[PDB]
Length: 88
Length: 98
Ligand SMILES: *[C@@H]1O[C@H](CO)[C@@H](O[C@@H]2O[C@H](CO)[C@@H](O)[C@H](O)[C@H]2NC(C)=O)[C@H](O)[C@H]1NC(C)=O
Ligand SMILES: *[C@@H]1O[C@H](CO)[C@@H](O)[C@H](O)[C@H]1NC(C)=O
Ligand SMILES: *[C@@H]1O[C@H](CO)[C@@H](O)[C@H](O)[C@H]1NC(C)=O
Image (tube, rainbow over all chains, first blue to last red; front, side, top):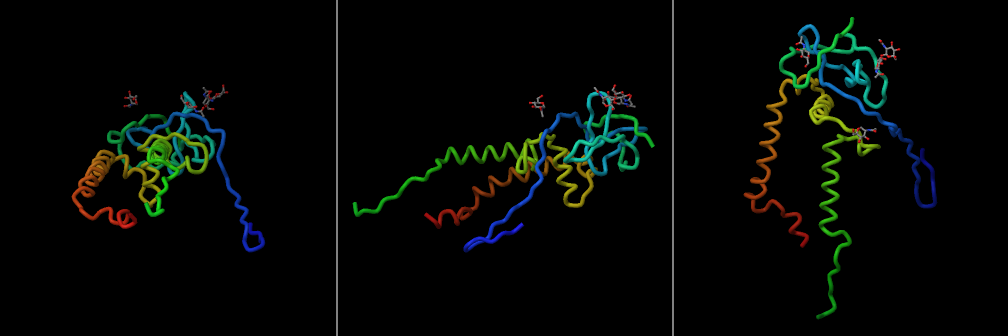
Protein backbone atom coordinates (compact mmCIF):
# COMPACT_ATOMS: atom_id res chain seq x y z
CA UNK A 1 0.00 0.00 0.00
CA UNK A 2 1.46 3.41 -0.93
CA UNK A 3 1.36 6.61 1.10
CA UNK A 4 2.66 10.11 0.40
CA UNK A 5 5.05 12.21 2.46
CA UNK A 6 6.78 15.60 2.05
CA UNK A 7 9.24 15.04 -0.80
CA UNK A 8 8.82 11.28 -0.83
CA UNK A 9 6.78 8.09 -0.72
CA UNK A 10 6.27 5.41 1.93
CA UNK A 11 5.43 1.79 1.10
CA UNK A 12 3.64 -0.61 3.46
CA UNK A 13 4.62 -4.13 2.39
CA UNK A 14 2.60 -7.14 3.58
CA UNK A 15 4.46 -10.44 3.83
CA UNK A 16 3.86 -14.05 4.89
CA UNK A 17 6.49 -15.62 7.17
CA UNK A 18 6.49 -19.29 8.28
CA UNK A 19 6.89 -20.25 11.92
CA UNK A 20 6.71 -23.17 14.37
CA UNK A 21 8.62 -25.74 12.33
CA UNK A 22 8.74 -29.45 13.12
CA UNK A 23 11.22 -32.25 12.41
CA UNK A 24 10.42 -35.15 10.09
CA UNK A 25 12.03 -38.06 8.25
CA UNK A 26 12.00 -37.87 4.46
CA UNK A 27 12.68 -40.09 1.45
CA UNK A 28 13.08 -39.20 -2.25
CA UNK A 29 10.76 -41.89 -3.65
CA UNK A 30 8.41 -44.70 -2.62
CA UNK A 31 8.91 -48.22 -3.96
CA UNK A 32 5.87 -50.41 -4.57
CA UNK A 33 5.33 -53.48 -6.77
CA UNK A 34 8.76 -52.95 -8.31
CA UNK A 35 7.98 -49.36 -9.36
CA UNK A 36 9.24 -46.05 -7.98
CA UNK A 37 6.70 -43.31 -7.22
CA UNK A 38 7.71 -39.62 -7.04
CA UNK A 39 5.52 -36.82 -5.65
CA UNK A 40 3.78 -34.38 -7.97
CA UNK A 41 3.66 -31.41 -5.57
CA UNK A 42 5.06 -31.82 -2.07
CA UNK A 43 7.51 -33.90 -0.07
CA UNK A 44 7.30 -37.31 1.57
CA UNK A 45 7.20 -37.28 5.37
CA UNK A 46 6.83 -39.73 8.25
CA UNK A 47 6.01 -39.27 11.92
CA UNK A 48 7.88 -42.48 12.77
CA UNK A 49 5.48 -45.26 11.75
CA UNK A 50 3.43 -44.29 8.68
CA UNK A 51 4.19 -42.29 5.54
CA UNK A 52 2.45 -39.23 4.10
CA UNK A 53 2.83 -36.67 1.32
CA UNK A 54 2.50 -32.98 2.22
CA UNK A 55 2.98 -29.55 0.71
CA UNK A 56 6.05 -27.38 1.24
CA UNK A 57 5.19 -24.33 3.38
CA UNK A 58 2.55 -26.02 5.55
CA UNK A 59 2.12 -29.34 7.36
CA UNK A 60 -0.97 -30.97 5.82
CA UNK A 61 -0.36 -34.73 5.67
CA UNK A 62 -2.37 -36.76 3.18
CA UNK A 63 -2.60 -40.46 2.35
CA UNK A 64 -0.37 -41.53 -0.54
CA UNK A 65 -2.38 -42.53 -3.62
CA UNK A 66 -1.73 -42.77 -7.35
CA UNK A 67 -3.48 -39.43 -7.92
CA UNK A 68 -0.58 -37.36 -6.52
CA UNK A 69 2.33 -39.57 -7.64
CA UNK A 70 3.87 -40.36 -11.03
CA UNK A 71 5.96 -43.50 -11.47
CA UNK A 72 8.34 -42.87 -14.41
CA UNK A 73 11.13 -45.31 -13.67
CA UNK A 74 12.30 -48.45 -11.87
CA UNK A 75 13.34 -49.34 -8.31
CA UNK A 76 17.08 -50.03 -8.59
CA UNK A 77 18.67 -46.70 -9.60
CA UNK A 78 17.41 -44.06 -7.12
CA UNK A 79 19.50 -43.64 -3.97
CA UNK A 80 17.65 -43.76 -0.66
CA UNK A 81 14.33 -45.25 -1.79
CA UNK A 82 12.03 -46.65 0.90
CA UNK A 83 9.25 -49.04 -0.03
CA UNK A 84 5.73 -48.58 1.26
CA UNK A 85 2.28 -49.51 0.05
CA UNK A 86 0.55 -47.07 -2.30
CA UNK A 87 -3.24 -47.26 -2.30
CA UNK A 88 -5.59 -46.58 -5.21
CA UNK B 1 54.05 15.16 4.60
CA UNK B 2 51.68 17.44 2.64
CA UNK B 3 48.45 16.80 4.55
CA UNK B 4 46.86 13.92 2.60
CA UNK B 5 45.94 10.80 4.57
CA UNK B 6 44.12 7.52 3.95
CA UNK B 7 41.69 6.19 6.59
CA UNK B 8 41.11 2.49 7.32
CA UNK B 9 37.79 0.74 6.65
CA UNK B 10 35.39 -0.07 9.46
CA UNK B 11 35.05 -3.76 8.54
CA UNK B 12 38.27 -5.76 8.59
CA UNK B 13 38.77 -8.56 6.07
CA UNK B 14 38.15 -11.19 8.76
CA UNK B 15 34.63 -9.87 9.36
CA UNK B 16 33.86 -9.94 5.62
CA UNK B 17 35.18 -13.50 5.43
CA UNK B 18 32.96 -14.47 8.37
CA UNK B 19 29.93 -12.93 6.63
CA UNK B 20 30.67 -14.79 3.39
CA UNK B 21 31.18 -18.10 5.22
CA UNK B 22 27.90 -17.62 7.09
CA UNK B 23 26.06 -17.00 3.82
CA UNK B 24 27.63 -20.07 2.21
CA UNK B 25 26.78 -22.35 5.14
CA UNK B 26 23.22 -21.02 5.27
CA UNK B 27 22.64 -21.54 1.55
CA UNK B 28 24.17 -25.03 1.68
CA UNK B 29 22.31 -26.44 4.71
CA UNK B 30 18.97 -24.61 4.29
CA UNK B 31 18.36 -23.82 0.60
CA UNK B 32 16.58 -20.48 0.21
CA UNK B 33 14.41 -20.57 3.35
CA UNK B 34 17.02 -18.80 5.50
CA UNK B 35 16.40 -15.60 3.51
CA UNK B 36 12.66 -15.46 4.26
CA UNK B 37 12.31 -16.79 7.82
CA UNK B 38 13.71 -19.46 10.12
CA UNK B 39 16.27 -21.76 8.55
CA UNK B 40 14.74 -25.14 7.68
CA UNK B 41 17.02 -28.11 7.07
CA UNK B 42 16.85 -30.20 3.89
CA UNK B 43 19.14 -32.82 2.30
CA UNK B 44 21.16 -31.45 -0.59
CA UNK B 45 19.99 -33.90 -3.32
CA UNK B 46 16.37 -32.96 -2.54
CA UNK B 47 17.27 -29.26 -2.78
CA UNK B 48 18.88 -29.92 -6.16
CA UNK B 49 15.77 -31.83 -7.25
CA UNK B 50 13.56 -28.87 -6.35
CA UNK B 51 15.89 -26.42 -8.10
CA UNK B 52 15.67 -28.67 -11.17
CA UNK B 53 11.87 -28.66 -10.89
CA UNK B 54 11.97 -24.87 -10.75
CA UNK B 55 13.22 -24.56 -14.35
CA UNK B 56 10.69 -26.97 -15.87
CA UNK B 57 12.57 -30.29 -15.71
CA UNK B 58 10.94 -33.01 -13.62
CA UNK B 59 12.53 -34.42 -10.47
CA UNK B 60 13.26 -37.91 -11.82
CA UNK B 61 15.87 -36.45 -14.19
CA UNK B 62 18.14 -35.76 -11.21
CA UNK B 63 17.59 -38.83 -9.02
CA UNK B 64 18.50 -41.10 -11.95
CA UNK B 65 21.54 -38.97 -12.91
CA UNK B 66 22.98 -37.93 -9.54
CA UNK B 67 26.54 -39.21 -10.01
CA UNK B 68 27.02 -37.63 -13.45
CA UNK B 69 25.71 -34.25 -12.26
CA UNK B 70 27.93 -34.38 -9.17
CA UNK B 71 31.00 -35.17 -11.29
CA UNK B 72 30.17 -32.37 -13.74
CA UNK B 73 29.74 -29.88 -10.88
CA UNK B 74 33.03 -30.94 -9.30
CA UNK B 75 34.93 -30.57 -12.58
CA UNK B 76 33.32 -27.19 -13.30
CA UNK B 77 34.32 -25.93 -9.85
CA UNK B 78 37.84 -27.30 -10.26
CA UNK B 79 38.48 -25.56 -13.58
CA UNK B 80 37.66 -22.15 -12.05
CA UNK B 81 40.89 -21.85 -10.05
CA UNK B 82 43.08 -22.60 -13.08
CA UNK B 83 41.04 -20.23 -15.24
CA UNK B 84 41.52 -17.45 -12.68
CA UNK B 85 45.25 -18.09 -12.29
CA UNK B 86 46.14 -18.47 -15.98
CA UNK B 87 44.33 -15.35 -17.19
CA UNK B 88 46.53 -12.28 -16.52
CA UNK B 89 43.83 -9.58 -16.58
CA UNK B 90 41.02 -11.40 -14.78
CA UNK B 91 40.67 -8.90 -11.91
CA UNK B 92 40.94 -5.66 -13.85
CA UNK B 93 37.87 -3.92 -12.42
CA UNK B 94 39.17 -4.17 -8.85
CA UNK B 95 42.67 -3.02 -9.86
CA UNK B 96 41.45 0.03 -11.79
CA UNK B 97 40.04 1.57 -8.59
CA UNK B 98 43.40 1.43 -6.80
C1 LIG C 1 1.54 -41.30 12.65
O1 LIG C 1 0.31 -41.02 11.96
C2 LIG C 1 -0.60 -42.13 11.92
C3 LIG C 1 -1.78 -41.69 11.09
O2 LIG C 1 -2.59 -40.75 11.79
C4 LIG C 1 -0.98 -42.55 13.33
O3 LIG C 1 -1.82 -43.69 13.28
C5 LIG C 1 -3.05 -43.40 13.98
O4 LIG C 1 -2.82 -43.21 15.39
C6 LIG C 1 -4.01 -42.88 16.12
C7 LIG C 1 -3.58 -42.63 17.55
O5 LIG C 1 -3.62 -43.82 18.33
C8 LIG C 1 -5.03 -44.02 16.00
O6 LIG C 1 -6.22 -43.64 16.67
C9 LIG C 1 -5.32 -44.30 14.53
O7 LIG C 1 -6.17 -45.44 14.42
C10 LIG C 1 -4.03 -44.56 13.77
N1 LIG C 1 -4.30 -44.75 12.35
C11 LIG C 1 -4.39 -45.96 11.79
C12 LIG C 1 -4.68 -45.98 10.32
O8 LIG C 1 -4.24 -47.00 12.44
C13 LIG C 1 0.27 -42.86 14.15
O9 LIG C 1 -0.09 -43.12 15.50
C14 LIG C 1 1.24 -41.68 14.10
N2 LIG C 1 2.46 -42.00 14.83
C15 LIG C 1 2.64 -41.68 16.12
C16 LIG C 1 3.96 -42.08 16.71
O10 LIG C 1 1.78 -41.10 16.77
C1 LIG D 1 15.35 -31.14 14.95
O1 LIG D 1 16.37 -31.95 15.54
C2 LIG D 1 17.61 -31.27 15.78
C3 LIG D 1 18.57 -32.30 16.32
O2 LIG D 1 17.94 -33.56 16.51
C4 LIG D 1 17.38 -30.11 16.74
O3 LIG D 1 18.60 -29.40 16.91
C5 LIG D 1 16.31 -29.18 16.19
O4 LIG D 1 16.02 -28.16 17.14
C6 LIG D 1 15.04 -29.96 15.87
N1 LIG D 1 14.04 -29.08 15.28
C7 LIG D 1 13.13 -28.41 16.00
C8 LIG D 1 12.18 -27.55 15.23
O5 LIG D 1 13.08 -28.50 17.22
C1 LIG E 1 12.09 -52.75 1.03
O1 LIG E 1 13.15 -52.07 1.70
C2 LIG E 1 13.74 -52.92 2.70
C3 LIG E 1 14.62 -52.06 3.59
O2 LIG E 1 15.57 -51.28 2.86
C4 LIG E 1 14.46 -54.07 2.02
O3 LIG E 1 15.04 -54.91 3.01
C5 LIG E 1 13.47 -54.87 1.17
O4 LIG E 1 14.17 -55.83 0.38
C6 LIG E 1 12.66 -53.95 0.25
N1 LIG E 1 11.58 -54.70 -0.39
C7 LIG E 1 11.75 -55.44 -1.49
C8 LIG E 1 10.51 -56.13 -2.01
O5 LIG E 1 12.83 -55.56 -2.05
